Image (cartoon, rainbow over all chains, first blue to last red; front, side, top):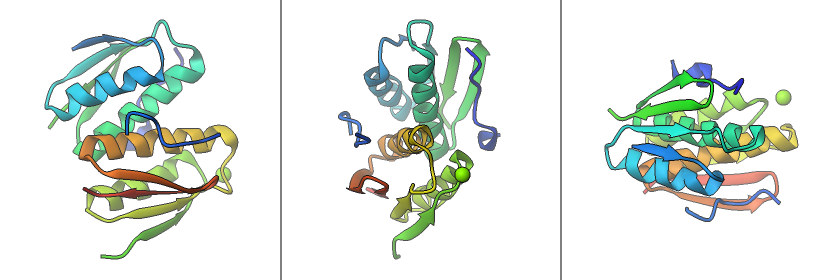
Length: 10
Length: 8
Length: 67
Length: 70
Ligand SMILES: [Mg+2]
C-alpha cells in the first residue's frame, strides 16, 4: 500500500 | 521465467 | 468500473474496460505487495499508451481515466 | 520506420519504450543491466502499452523483448 503512480505519468 | 502475459 | 483484483490476470479486466473508453477504479486489498506492484506497472502502461490519467485514491485504490 | 533499440538501466527507462511505441514504432529492449524485479516491472509496463494499443509483444530471449504496433 506504499505504491504510487510512476512519476513520469505526470 | 519472464514471459509474455497470457492475455496478450 | 469497480474491479476487485484477485491476481495479476485481473489486469485484463482493467485493460479491457479502459481501452474501450471507460474509467476504471480498482481495488488491490486482496493482492500481495508484489502483485499490486505488477498491477500498477500494467495500469501505468495502459495510461501511457493512450495518454490517460492515473491517480491513487487511497492506499489500495487507484483509477485509470481515458482521453 | 525501423525498430528502436533500448538498453534499460532503470524502470524510468520504460518511457523510451512507451514514447517510441505510441509514436507507431517497434521497440526492441534489452534488460541485461536490470535486476530480476526491474525486468518484471518493464515487462508488465510493456504489456500495458501493448494491450492498450492492440500491439504485439514477443520474447526474443530471457533479457530481450519487442513491442510491435498494430
Ligand atoms: Mg540500473
